[PDB]
Amino acid sequence: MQVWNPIDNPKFETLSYLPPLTDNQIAREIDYMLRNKWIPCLEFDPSGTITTLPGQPGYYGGRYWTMWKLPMFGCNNAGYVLREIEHCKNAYPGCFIRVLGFDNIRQVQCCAFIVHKP
Amino acid sequence: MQVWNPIDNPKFETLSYLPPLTDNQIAREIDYMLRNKWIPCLEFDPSGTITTLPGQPGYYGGRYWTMWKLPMFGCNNAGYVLREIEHCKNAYPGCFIRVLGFDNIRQVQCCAFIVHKP
Amino acid sequence: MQVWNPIDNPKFETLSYLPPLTDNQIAREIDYMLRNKWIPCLEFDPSGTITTLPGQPGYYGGRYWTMWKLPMFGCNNAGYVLREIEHCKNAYPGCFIRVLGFDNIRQVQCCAFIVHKP
Amino acid sequence: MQVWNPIDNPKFETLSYLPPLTDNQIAREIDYMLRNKWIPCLEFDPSGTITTLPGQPGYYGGRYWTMWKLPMFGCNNAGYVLREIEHCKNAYPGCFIRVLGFDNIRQVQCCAFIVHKP
Image (cartoon, rainbow over all chains, first blue to last red; front, side, top):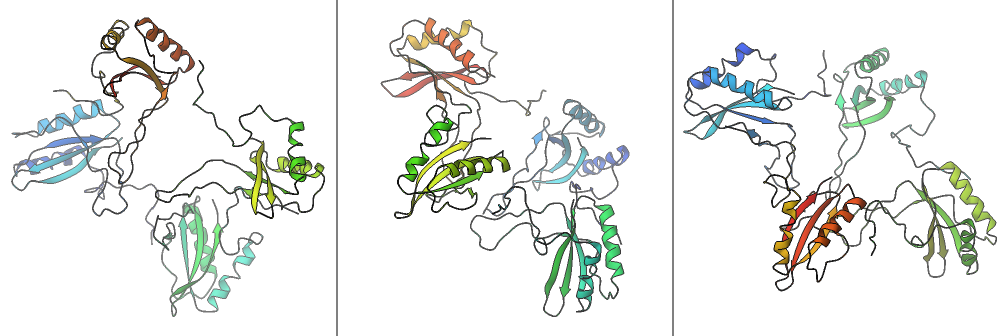
């Protein structure tokens, strides 16, 4: 029998229950988005809390982050996405950073995972 | 004439107005729960405050604590409950700890008292 | 022309716009309450702020203080009220203190002023 | 491509997106108010934040400041407005300061800009 820790144990959605992610395993999730013709993007924010309202169902605060430059339309190689992450983290070394993708035919995001923590 | 102190004087429900509890007087409240065929349990939480809501009668926040492992079904000797409290005290030396009992025929708790303070 | 200061300038109701009160001028407001057959009392509290509620007219929080021992029924000399203030000042040297009076025929207070500040 | 900074970048309404203001171009915005027959005034406050209410459209908190002495009725030279700003700066060296103007025929303010920051 073992006990799960309730104090100071935050989580960050998908892939947060596995061992930490290495640099190889990161450029295998981008070649899967490129093989299906999706569009990469980047974001950053200094905090991650959630706020509500008294009597309004389905309203939450803290779901929008700030966009780095613009979506990378017409991209074929995975060596540019990896270089943009390094430019992002040299200017803001005290924020979180997250990677997304875009399906343009169904208009919905397809991926999300964290690559940097403060 | 004497004056009761209003500053920094919290209380913790049953048995809090008596002198502090010794190790002998603790293993006399367990032999009374065992003589009536009840089931022991343990809990712990870092805080103890209470919160309310504007216009909802009978709603309070801060009434659930975290359970240690599981209720001790089929227990006859009082030397195991005393050993589990010591295992609980080494993992979390900065929390409160409470002892409970269960009546399975009327479905209601039967006792509660505090054994450790931060 | 001169300017009235808006920063860090609290006030405490009646008699608070006059120069500070000396020990002589304090035992002249008690002989005026005793000449009309009223009953002295004492109070103390650590804070002095006021709160409200969203949509309830005439509700304010922070209007009750704590009472020292009991009202002084049947008191004729002013040397006891002055001695009780000194007993109150040694037990709680970090609170405010107020002096009250009671009219028992119209059931309403008649006086109030501050004698000690933290 | 360049990125606009989202962290710790407050703004103060009109003329805040231009380079900082020198002493020459502070005595050119007053001769424009004097040529149209308007009335100068001054203000100061220690903070600059805004607050709202749950369900009341068009209500905001933090829109009133404190007035220095009085509006300058019948003023023709711009050397008095410049001297009053210096008297205001020695008494309260930890507040913001604003300059206003008044049109008495349409009853509406005509300008506002900041001249001192903490």
